[PDB]
Length: 115
RNA sequence: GAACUUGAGUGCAGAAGAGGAGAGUGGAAUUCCACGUGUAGCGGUGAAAUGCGUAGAGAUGUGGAGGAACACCAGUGGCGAA
Image (cartoon, rainbow, N blue to C red):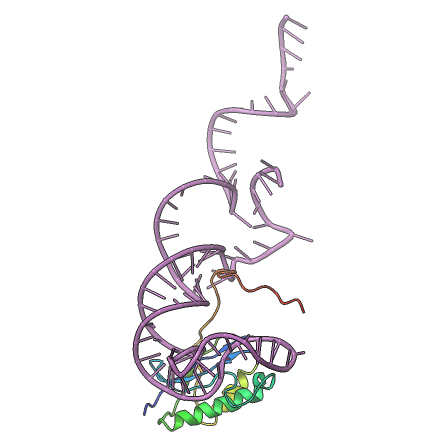
């Protein structure tokens, strides 16, 4: 029953993560995009981000979690709503991380969709 | 045939440059493998499904292997005959 923990913001066009883990990155409860029986486009809404974040928060409160250190890693779709949901309990976002390649074209990305 | 120095070279003194060839080296990210935590989805689309997941995926942490390309700098900026 651990006091402190982490969550991990990493946002794209329509993908975001924020799982509830311990200080050393051992998991406890998890939040990332959906998880909650939502499907399709509803899954990527800001609303559905809240309900995923609440459900992982209320999972971790039962493990005696009081505070959540969260990261920063660019803007995206439903990142702000996911934080608002977590501020039911209350917490901080101190760290700032990144998912970027130090080469433009480190690995070659997949081809542009013709739509 | 004789001159000349404006062309064209040489000498001398500076300058900038992703010009080229060779050898070595670095960090970020992806992938795979191993392991810890954890558990039911993940992923994807206009909407789906095939896929991948309880033989424990996805997420998260740590380490290992390997290849390729070089964020920011970076600019009708530079260099090059192209």
